[PDB]
Image 1 (cartoon, rainbow over the protein chains, first blue to last red):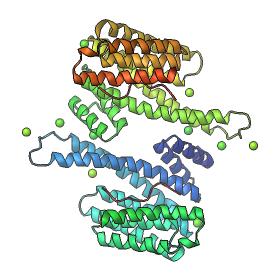
Image 2: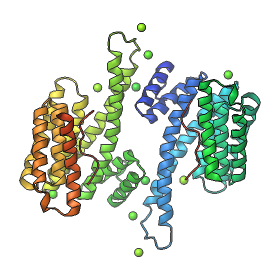
Image 3: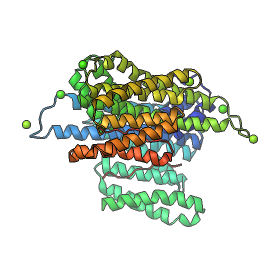
Image 4: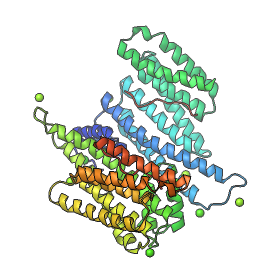
Length: 236
Length: 236
Length: 10
Length: 10
Ligand SMILES: [Ca+2]
Ligand SMILES: [Ca+2]
Ligand SMILES: [Ca+2]
Ligand SMILES: [Ca+2]
Ligand SMILES: [Cl-]
Ligand SMILES: [Cl-]
Ligand SMILES: [Mg+2]
Ligand SMILES: [Mg+2]
Ligand SMILES: [Mg+2]
Ligand SMILES: [Mg+2]
């Protein structure tokens, strides 16, 4: 890999610089290089990895949606034939997106997840695994769609089971995991009732634990709780 | 080139799609491919080329500024030594930026400018030539800085001379050219008085020709005139 | 309007 | 605050 000659600490330093410069592709490459050093990641380092790839894939998802919408409109009755270009370019963006997802899943499998023993790291990585299978699911068409959905579900479920056993209901990782699993249910799995139930229970159990928290932890937890509430408003 | 197998019309179609998807790197590659077909560009096509590369280089310039600022702060007295990483990463971004500038200048030289005979195309391309030398000048340090500045000045000047002879004072290309040449004077050439004088004269001569214009042309011209005024407010 | 997922935050 | 140059427009 191109980052094989750079020190781990230098890669982390440059990832932080790239974040400041809003150079997320570079940030992702630097964090990939850091992971490939083979050492476990700290909490801050895990978060850098997450931010970098979320921003990269986020760009791709937004683009793919634009192109997919144009494509669907071309396939309506009364629409003028414009040749293969829309499909071709949507396919190009889609392939790049799938490549980014595969890269992240590869890092998790080789070997972040297997070395992660603490609840905070293991849940973080398993949530990521769910997330990147969910992003694959967004663009998947057919039966391979089914296996991708099941892979996302399985990762989220394993993460949920650990988080419920090992973390307080207000833990931001636990909250973010439940939020994203609820989005999976609603947006991917055609299970809006499961989504609503999960969001409601997550919100209520966190509410009841807020009293245990410092002012700063309270702010961190309530930020994510508000997103659960925003979704419940959207969904009901 | 990677776009050598794609039809010119397909490249233009995909450039427009990439613009809608905010995929400006792709948009630039598609327009590069289109230019390399060897045919002159229409007005709309010239504008696609301009938008694509402006957005790419715009990203790079913003990043370079962030990194350069961090770097300067590291070199102040009392700043802790953090090793070569800031300089290295600024250099990386800088090199990529210079590469993008060189690519655009290459397209203009091979062979857009030499085939451009109408005032609207020739002024457009010469303004671009000025602009991309100006972007090189922003990051240049030393005597090569001087030759780069002179290259920008020369391109702008040739464009100005043609625009003054061949276009009305309200022509948007003419206005945009004068705006950018004024920015060159103020920001690059250490000539704020030249900048102010140019902006003022450009604004006043356009004001006096507005009466000749349709409602839509009036809107197009006054939009750029407002930028001249915004700069004069900033500069005085 | 799509559902909101977890944003970039610690 | 840097000077404004020509934006993306026709
Ligand atoms: Ca076509
Ligand atoms: Ca371990
Ligand atoms: Ca260092
Ligand atoms: Ca010609
Ligand atoms: Cl394509
Ligand atoms: Cl670097
Ligand atoms: Mg028809
Ligand atoms: Mg495909
Ligand atoms: Mg000290
Ligand atoms: Mg350099």
